[PDB]
Each structure stands twice: as C-alpha cells, then as structure tokens.
Amino acid sequence: PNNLKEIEQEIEKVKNEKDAAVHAQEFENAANLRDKQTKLEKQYEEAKNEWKNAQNGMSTSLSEEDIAE
Amino acid sequence: MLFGRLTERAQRVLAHAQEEAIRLNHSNIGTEHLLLGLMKEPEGIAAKVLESFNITEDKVIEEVEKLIGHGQDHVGTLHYTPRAKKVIELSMDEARKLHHNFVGTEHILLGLIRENEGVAARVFANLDLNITKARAQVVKALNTPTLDSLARDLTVIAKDGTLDPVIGRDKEITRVIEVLSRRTKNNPVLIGEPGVGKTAIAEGLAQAIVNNEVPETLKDKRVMSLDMGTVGEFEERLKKVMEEIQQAGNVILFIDLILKPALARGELQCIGATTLDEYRKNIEKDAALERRFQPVQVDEPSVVDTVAILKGLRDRYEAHHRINISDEAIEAAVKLSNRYVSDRFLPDKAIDLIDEASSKVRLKSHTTPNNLKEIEQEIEKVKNEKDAAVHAQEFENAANLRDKQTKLEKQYEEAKNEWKNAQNGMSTSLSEEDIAEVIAGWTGIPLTKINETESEKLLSLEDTLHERVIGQKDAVNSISKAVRRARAGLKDPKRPIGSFIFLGPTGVGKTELARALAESMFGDDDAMIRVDMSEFMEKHAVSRLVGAPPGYVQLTEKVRRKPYSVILFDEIEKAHPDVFNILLQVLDDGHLTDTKGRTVDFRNTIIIMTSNVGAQELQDQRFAGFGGSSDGQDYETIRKTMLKELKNSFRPEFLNRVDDIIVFHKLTKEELKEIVTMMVNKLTNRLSEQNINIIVTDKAKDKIAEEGYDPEYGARPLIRAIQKTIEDNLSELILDGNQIEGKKVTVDHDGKEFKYDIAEQ
Amino acid sequence: VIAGWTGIPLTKINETESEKLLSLEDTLHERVIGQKDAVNSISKAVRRARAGLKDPKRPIGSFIFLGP
Amino acid sequence: NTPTLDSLARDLTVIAKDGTLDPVIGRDKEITRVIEVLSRRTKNNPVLIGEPGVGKTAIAEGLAQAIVNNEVPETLKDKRVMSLDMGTVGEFEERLKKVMEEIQQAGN
Ligand SMILES: Nc1ncnc2c1ncn2[C@@H]1O[C@H](COP(=O)(O)OP(=O)(O)O)[C@@H](O)[C@H]1O
C-alpha cells in the first residue's frame, strides 16, 4: 500500500551510503548510518505487520463484476 | 540502478553543476560545469586524490576559463550535453570494475578524465594527469549444477544493471505472472512471429524480480533459460535436470520446441516461445498438453507506443555517439521506417535506423577539414629531409630544418585546439533529413519523393495523374475525390483505401492509369501486383492465391511483403464464383488470414478490378446512329445506365460494397496527337547522354497517328507504329559511327513518307 | 592471347561491333534462305535495343517463333 | 598486449603499418561502410559476404590501411587488426577459450 515501498527504498540507499563510508574509512559517519538503518528496519517490521494484520480483517471474495471484466 | 547508487556527495556535485551553468549563462550543462562543482566538495575520496597531486580549486578555475566560452542562454530545459551523459556512463561502468555497488565523487573524477573529448578532459591532460596515473592513486587511498550445465540464468544478469530497460511490455509482464498464479494452465506460451521480441519478455520479467515489483508469490525465483541448440544420451540429461528443479522449487524454465508427465504433475512452469504454426501442429492435437498451456499473444507495439520506447533509449544512445538527438527526429524516424521497411516490425527496426543515422553524421563531422592534414604533411617532409642531412653531415643545414620543423609543430597544436574549440561550440544535433537519406539508400526511392509531406501531394493528385495519363478527365476527378476522402478519415479505417471497377474499351489506358496512381501515391511505378483471372476459373483456383491448404504443397505472400501496393484484378467478369466470396470479405473486413494463421493487412492497398462487360454496351451507343454517339450525355447518367448491365452479371451485394464505378471513354484523333507527344518526351530523356532533341511536326504526328488508328484495339498499335518508323531510322544514325552527336533531328511528313531532316542542336 | 585461349577468330576480335549489325541481314540470309519478313523484323529490332532505346536491364532479345 | 592472440592468430595491422603490401584501391565504398558500422552501438559487428574469389581477404587490408593513414576517427583509434587462422584450429576448444580471455580484457 505505497508505504513499505518507499521505506524499503530508504533502507537500500542507506546501505549504499554506509558502504561508501566503509570504503572511505569515514567511520564517524558510518556509525551514525548503522544506527539509522536499525531505526528504519525497526519501523519497517511494525509497518509490515500491521498491514498484513489489517488484511485479515476483510475477506476478498469474487463477484459477477470481476468475471464480467 | 542510477538513483539508488549515487551517494549524497555525488548528488551535491550535480546540484553544484546546475548552478554553475546559471552563473556562466549556458542553456546546456557541459562537462566543464561538472569540474567546477567537483572542487566545491572537498570531503570525498576524489578530493584526497587531487590533494596528493597538489591540485587546488583556484588553479583549475583559471585553467578552464581559458577556453570556457560564453554566450546567450535560454532558461528552462537545462539538459546535459551529449558528451556529459557519456561521463556518467563511464563513471558508473568504472564502479563495477572495482566491484562497487555505489557511485561517489571518487568515480565522477575517474570518469571525467576518460571522456578524452570534453573540456574537463583537456584540463587534466594539461596537468600531466592521465587515466593510469589516477587509477592506481585512488586504489591505495581506498544449486542444481546439472541444470546450470546446459542453461543460462537471466535475473543474475539483470541484477548487474547492464541490461537496457525494457519498456512497453508492462501489459505483458503482468499478464505472464497472472497465468502463473493459477492451478490449471499455469504454463503460459508466448505466440507470435519470430523476431518481434519474444525473448525480450523474459528480460522484462527478470528486471521486475530484481526491482521487487512481483508479489510475494513470485518473489526470489531463479529465472532460467535453456537453449534449443544444447541438445539415449540426450534423454539421460533431462531426467537429472528435472529432479534438481523439483528440489529447488523456484526455478522458472524458458524454452523455445519425456517431459509430458512432468507438466501433467505440475513439476515445471516452462514458458515456451514457439511459433503459431508449430503450436497448432505439435501441441493443439495433444489434449493433455492443451489443458496445461495458456497461449499469450505477443504483438508489435503501436506507432505511438514506439515513440515512448525510443525516448527511453534516447539518453543511452546520446552517450555512445555523443550526438544530440531531437524529439522531432525520433518521431520521423519511426514513422518512415514503418512506412517503407516491412520486414522486421517495431521497435527492433527503428532502433537501428537511428543508430546508423547518428553514426553517419558522427563520421562526417569528426574527420579533419583539411586543416591539420596540410600541416601534418609539412611536418613530415621536413623530418625526412633533416634525417638525410644528418647522413650528409650537414649540421648547419639541419639547424635551419630544426627551427622550421619546431615552428610547424608549434602551429599544429594551435590549429588543433581552435578546431576542436569550434566543434564544442555548436551542437551536433540530428535532423530528420539525415534519417531520410539513410532510408532512401535502402530502397532507391528519390530523396525528393520521401521528403514529400503527403499533404499537398493528395491535393495535387489530379494534376500528377494527368502527367502520365491523357484524356478521360472524368475518371481522374472521381478517383481523386474518392482517395482523398478515405485518407481524410471519412471512411472506416479497417476498410481498404479504395475499391473501383474499370470499364470501357480495352487497351485505352486502363493499365496505364493504375501505374500512374501507384507511382504518385506510393512513390514507385512498379509497386503493383497484377493478378489476372485467366488461371482462376475452377473451384480449386481459390486454394492458390490464399496458399496451399494443409496436406498439400500466392497472393497473400505478395501483399504481405509489400503492404503499400495497388492490386489489379483483370478479367474479373470471368472468374470462379468462390473467388468473389473472398473479394467481398476483403472489402468489408479489410484483412485476411492464410492457412498458416498469419493475418495480412489491406488498410494500405487500393483494389482495382477490370471487367470487359459494359464495353459492348458503350460501343452500341456509339453505333446507335450513323455519325452520332452519346458522349454529350451527363457522366452520372452514363454511370447509371452501365450500372444496370453491371448488376445483371454480378451480385448487387458485391456492387454496394464497391466505393465507385469508373467507365472509360473512347479516343479521338485530336487526343491521339497528344499521346505521341508524351512518348516523344519519354524517348528524348531515354538517350539523355547524347543530348539530342527531336521535334516532330503536326502533319507528321497526324500521319503516324492514323497509321495505328484502330478503335477496336484502342491506342495499342500507336506505340508499335513509332517503334517501326522513328526508332528504326534513329538507331541506324547512331550505328553509323555516331552520325549525330548532340544534334537536333526534325521529322516532317513531306506527303510521301517522314522526311528525316538532319541538323544540329 | 585471347584468340589462343578459347579459339576466337582474330577477325572477330578486330571487329568494332559497329558494322556487324549492318551486315546482319546478309549473314542471316546466308544460312536462312527466304522468309525475308522474319529476317528484316529482327534485324531492325536489335539495333534499337543496342542503341539504348530499350531499357538496359531488360534483355536485348525476346521473341517467340511460330511455324513447323 | 594479448601475447597468446599474437601466436595463435596472424596480425595484419603490423604489415599495414610497414606498408609492404600493395594498397587496396577501388574498394572505397566497402571501407567507408565498415567503419560506419563499427561506430554504431547495436549490431556493430559487420560480416563480409561475397562470392569466394572476389578477394574478400584483401578487403580487410584496406581497413587497416586507414588506421595507418590515421583517417579513421578517434573511436577506431588503437585497434589491432587480428585475423584468426583455421590451421591452428575438447582440445580444439582449449585454444579459443584461452585467447578470448586476453581479448576481452584488452578491449582494443
Ligand atoms: N497517356 C495516355 N492516355 C491514354 N492512353 C494511354 C496513355 N498511355 C498509354 N495509353 C494506352 O493504354 C494502353 C494500355 O493497354 P492495356 O490496358 O494493358 O490493354 P489490356 O486492357 O488489353 O490489357 C496502351 O496500349 C496505351 O496505348
């Protein structure tokens, strides 16, 4: 639902940014990025779990409209 | 994988370069703008590399300001120069060389020096810095094996990002995964003609897997393809492979003709790509296989769709050739390639057309314009002379030669620098005219014919037809109005361009008019497929034009290869009735399907049928009275009367589907005079090398016109009369050791025969 | 050299191919006595094609003969 | 410098550099077409097609001639003209696999 998409993208760019710091020996910034990534993943798990939890709230059923299409 | 790899420092470099162009008043961001913004971020690895080289920000500011160049600019559409985009491709490529998944400022400087043509490239060269010196400087500062034996993974390659972004297949990528998520018939088979890009579908799906767009049900699956050429011994290999795939559980097979039980048990999810003809012959007959495959049709993208596809790849080609490509150039390229080339479909044929167009203009504007070649010869000749002087112990003479040669080399660099500075001043954009040149060579069509805008050509069709056809203006007006209505859009697009019936005396211009129409519309005289009903009289004749029926060993093949042509059906009044049934289908449906299932098109064709009926009715009007005729009646009145005879022999249902009916008149003495006039002009241009002008008097023209005068045979004998009279005498003059050379020959009938007055031009 | 390669007569080589056509009528009647109409018709046709009146791509000679 | 390619294949750009053989004259369109194809991005690998006996091998000499003349653009600069010999070619495929490693790395 257009939420875990962008959140996952931020995790990707953060990981690349940390890799650049590691190869450049900029460990001062790398330490901050490591904690930031953990923050992103922590909220990522909660956001995904609540989404699938709400998915079970409603049941997807077919209808003659779908077959008509 | 561009935005996802550029680090924050690299992103700030692009932002700095954008405002550098604003300060310098440039409407396009050049390579030199990247260098200016690069020095404003002294934190990256590249900053350390230049630091060890004692290269400061201000030193390169004045270095680039020597040949910066200044001019006017337009706010908006501040794109990158064709060379600038090549730098980004180079820097990203160098990242994979070092096995880096990120692109930073350390790679921006690495790629800048590899351009070798840009402004920034020369700045580094002037500081005795090359690619090799900076290369090592930054280095120190920094499973189903049997299945894999005869196959190739695809999503692994797509992970690298080297694959071009497949566009326009989104409706089919979703379609394929839709078929997969089914309990039955979960094995889609792509059906289409070869070369339309069926293999490109697999790459698009694998790209979505890497990009994380497929749902969880289609997440983390190894895309695998098996080549048909990899094949007792053959049977042993496949048995081992299928067992391994069953263990993995996420291997998607890709094939292109034992294994039937494997698919019946739901063990494999192969995606075939065989042709329609083979599918109906080897798969359709098998009921078990039929219940396990869902064919998916693969079609050529539309013209408007191809525009978007080419725009996506436009940036990629702008880097390789360093050639600016305009938007209007792309739309012209695809439309013209589809219009004339009809052998490879879109977009695989439009991509190469713009590829050769960019390369062609690249070579012409790259070679030295005879400014450094002359100087190079001067340097070379002095060197050889000086070497010979050394062997002669001419030390004093060699001293003068040394000074001269040094001066020549001094001017050589100056001329090269100013020549390339001027080259960088302008943009080597691509024009649609250049594209028209390449396609013109591919077909031999004159560039003027291709350059026609198709708008005024339709308006002036009446005049153009009169050039090659003389007389019967009523026929010309009716057909010209008919075709311009269909092209204007007033007719159903699926219906053919036009359908007509030609009547009147035989050999009066019926064939010539069709040739003239084909030349004027389609730009070629021989763009006609003449078909005569002489061979089509029996019922079995229908199995000839449509192709051989199954179990056995024409027209559909010809029209498919030339979608833009004029089809002529002579002797339509004498044909098998079953052939008429096919004709009615073509007029309304607008397309046909052969025995092989391939569908031909008729929306770019004009159908003309020649019938011998009604001609005897017309001559009955000519012989109704002794010395009179019915030419003074209204043209529509004659059309109504002839329609009665036309419906007498044919079916009224067929006639109602015909756009218009054309009836040709007779020929008179005055008309025949102008007929020979055209042929004289044609023959004059025939021997254009000799440059000989022939003028025939009116009396001589009338003398030969009546010689071939035969209303029964029309104007057919007229051509033969000229061949036996003027050609025979003229040829003998040339055979006599070129008797006439650039002279003028006048033919005047003196009362007995044609007096061949021999004179000069 | 060419005469000794394929046995071509030297006189034929010396011909300029400009008067052979002029004497075609005499040569044809040497082996085909009579039927003058069949000889003059084809003799006056080859000159037109060789002069360049006909299309160069199309073959010079194209005829169908009738009779026993 | 692809040492294995030099041994298992014949090098022609060196011969063209010395100019010992007669220059190719008359094949102006063929040479200009090949360089045009090599400057393309897609399908930029031309293949010479002709009847056996029109000296297609001699045509390849003209391409190397332009390099020595320094007439080809910067894109074609520094490209050794190497021709494989069928005399040298399991064990058959060992040689081709060994040579292709150096060719890809060199890139010129
Ligand atoms: N400009 C012209 N105007 C009128 N008639 C022409 C013109 N040019 C050629 N023709 C005539 O058109 C005729 C075409 O004959 P054609 O229709 O093929 O005969 P058939 O109908 O028996 O096949 C030629 O014999 C020629 O004399």
Image: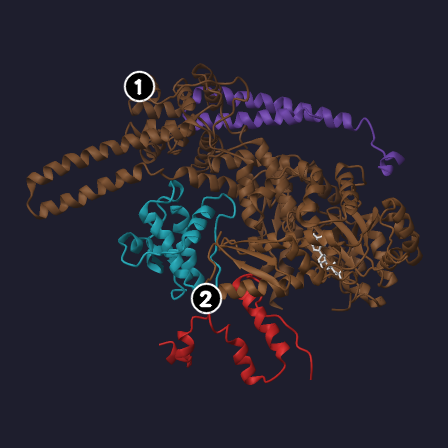
Q: Chain D is drawn in which colour?
A: cyan
Chain letter of the residue beneath label 1 in the structure image = B
- The answer to whether residue B401 shows anywhere in this view is yes
Residue B746 picture quarter: bottom right
Q: Chain C is drawn in which colour?
A: red
Label 2 vs label 1: CA separation?
62 Å
Residue B577 x %, y %: 88, 61
Q: Is mark 1 within 8 Å of ligand 1?
A: no
Q: Colour of chain B?
A: brown
Residue at 73% in and 51% down: B670
Q: Colour of chain A?
A: purple
- Few, some or many C-alpha atoms within 10 Å of disc 2 (few <14, some 14-19, many ≥20)? few
Q: In which quarter of the image is ligand 1?
A: bottom right
Local secondary structure at mark 1: helix
Residue at 43% in and 35% down: B94
The tag on residue B497 is none
- Few, some or many C-alpha atoms within 10 Å of disc 1 (few <14, some 14-19, many ≥20)? few
Give the side of residue B744 with respect to residue B547, left or right.
left
State the residue in front, B501 or C21.
C21
Q: Mark 2 points at which residue?
A: D52
Residue B390 x %, y %: 10, 45
Chain letter of the residue beneath label 2 in the structure image = D
Q: In this view, does B582 lie above or below A25?
A: below
Q: In this view, does B105 lie above or below B355?
A: above
State the residue in front, B176 or A47.
B176
Q: Which amino acid does label 1 sit on?
A: Lys
Q: In this view, does B107 lie above or below B586?
A: above
Colouring chosen for the image of the structure:
by chain
Residue at 49% in and 43% down: D41
State the residue in front, B98 or B379.
B379
Q: Mark 1 points at which residue?
A: B59
Furthest toward the top, the residue is B23
